[PDB]
Amino acid sequence: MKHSLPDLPYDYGALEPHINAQIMQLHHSKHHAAYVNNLNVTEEKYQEALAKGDVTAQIALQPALKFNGGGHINHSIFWTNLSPNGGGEPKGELLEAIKRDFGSFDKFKEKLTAASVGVQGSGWGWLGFNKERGHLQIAACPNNDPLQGTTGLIPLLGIDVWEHAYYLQYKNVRPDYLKAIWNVINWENVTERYMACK
Amino acid sequence: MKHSLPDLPYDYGALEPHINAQIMQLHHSKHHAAYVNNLNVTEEKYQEALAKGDVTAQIALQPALKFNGGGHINHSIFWTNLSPNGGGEPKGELLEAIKRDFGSFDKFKEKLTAASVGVQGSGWGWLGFNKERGHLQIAACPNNDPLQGTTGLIPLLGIDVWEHAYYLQYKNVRPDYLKAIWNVINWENVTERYMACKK
Ligand SMILES: [K+]
Ligand SMILES: [K+]
Ligand SMILES: [K+]
Ligand SMILES: [Mn+2]
Ligand SMILES: [Mn+2]
Image 1: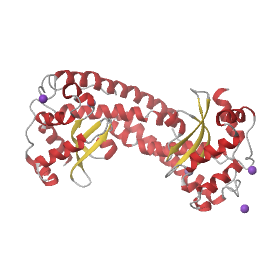
Image 2: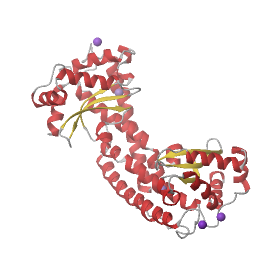
Image 3: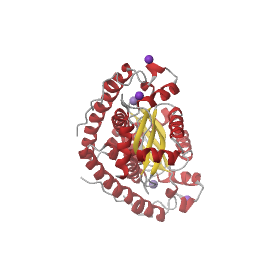
Image 4: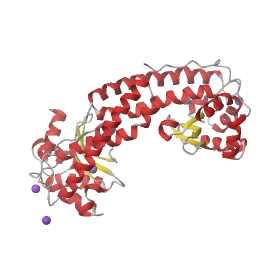
């Protein structure tokens, strides 16, 4: 009945040298912890305002709900999208879909990189599934706005481009972080999410 | 719970010739009614989502909640802000505050007119009360975003500048609508809302 912080499925240092253990520990144990806690606080406030029919209070809570709820949604997916066992290319129908919809795996990587580099301020780049069209789709989201809740696309792979996702290690050079992160993408998890859509 | 469409404080033609009866009837019986109906549907969907801990669903419902919920909030205030016995100027402490914060009643009208005419697309112009600062403040809101829920200001007087608020009568000439509406402002209601902000 309450949202909880999922354990990281690997050690804080498991993604070194691509994302260092200081980032992983802060990102999970400080940043995500705060979203979950503030999400639960906001949800309780929203339950009270709903039961009273206080629409002003409901609307005033929307920023916190989207930001912290989106934070919890996005980071929960993000941790499973990475793995010490990741890197390389997907296989099977996910790879065939990537080649069909984006031309090639490398072309897909440069489109998702571009979407991720192009976020001005805080946000996320996403590979999603468009269930209406039955094909893959790339989108960028601001701050912690979550993909499915704001666009209807089913999330397959997210890349956090908030500065806390990379700054300690890569400083201002966001492209260096994006170069590195391809080495730890958990294509097994992205594949499972894709198959679940179809 | 279940929100309801409030009765109008007067009949649909009571604000003529400034806002014609066809507009008032559509505005209350069709537009506000739809906000209530869609607000109730959206609240029930949010109750289901909360019980499931479905945060995606909660967030997907926010546009409909803000739009219809804000529509309900704003129009409920709007109807009480107008009156067949309105027009003229406020008195007492509200008039004192208007002179103090905007210089004069006429300069206040200019500023609220300008904010309302300046909305690009659908929206509202508002005179509000800033509780933190203890003075009056003019703001504009897009679409049906409600004043207090999005800015913290307490609404005193709102002017709907959605096209459905004036188009049938004034067509594209929103400034003529703004000039006419001053004739039906219920300063008694605005005063009540102001006094409530500070006792
Ligand atoms: K590196
Ligand atoms: K006339
Ligand atoms: K009058
Ligand atoms: Mn993050
Ligand atoms: Mn309206």
